[PDB]
Length: 332
Ligand SMILES: O=P(O)(O)O[C@H]1[C@@H](OP(=O)(O)O)[C@@H](OP(=O)(O)O)[C@@H](OP(=O)(O)O)[C@@H](OP(=O)(O)O)[C@H]1OP(=O)(O)O
Image 1: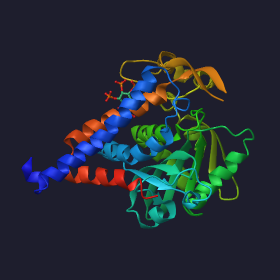
Image 2: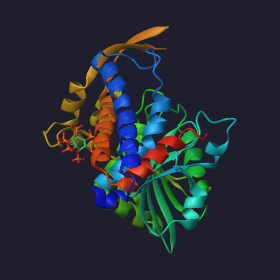
Image 3: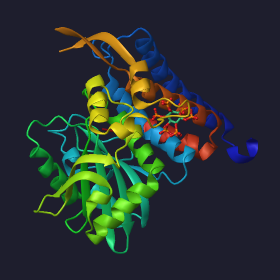
Image 4: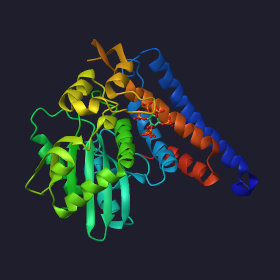
């Protein structure tokens, strides 16, 4: 091991210990809460702070575990407004305009922060320009006209000549699970790389989006494609972490063919897996007892487990890089 240490075996070892120490610290706390069926918000646990700090490290690990994922943290311009935003962007996050301008041509996934909420994205950039497919894990808008302006603002961030599709999906119910959900969606995008790529071509050629999705419309101010029904592009595997049982149930009721496909290697269907994750606990409105799927909180724990294992045996430059990312979370 000394060969790759470059003579700082002590510093590398201590920084490795420090990173695994933090991950294991967060992991332990999250595991205690989940095992005891306890709401984090009622337990005074600050998931938002922990999610923001671990997220750059999760991206490093996921990129290494899946070569080609090419996951990049991005933020919209409003995320740079310290007066309105809930949190500053995660460490290493890049402004969209800056990314689009200077990034090497290729295929990217992204988690995109607007200052208070995070979405997932699949991005294709080449000589002809940039096309992006945005999937929002949250779908809370009463009037479905608010999504039209969402599609615009995203397309505006990438430039008006960029092709854009905006797909709001009813997955998130809590207020703080957008980051982990978007990370999961990014991974699924990589999983369905060819399906999203085909959609990119259609967007770039101005073809019929109905070859990829069930219901779509052009916004007609930027020409962005708003997708109010993403199936089959948004399949059962992307609905796995649905927090409300009714969201999963309603989805299957709307796309019955998705109810029998296996969503993991243990051959569970979406319904079987969701039912397995159902819990009943007190949360905050003072308190409310509800039934929902704790699938997301398990996912966060699984991701931390991955990240910790990766750091344990990661090469020294990676340890350095992840230690710095952890430290830089305190710069804003
Ligand atoms: O690579 P994938 O086929 O996409 O599935 C992997 C994972 O793989 P490994 O355990 O072998 O490392 C699990 O897969 P299973 O063993 O259960 O089949 C898991 O799935 P479950 O949570 O349902 O158990 C999870 O998937 P998910 O986040 O959708 O729940 C995860 O997926 P990712 O690679 O996207 O992180």
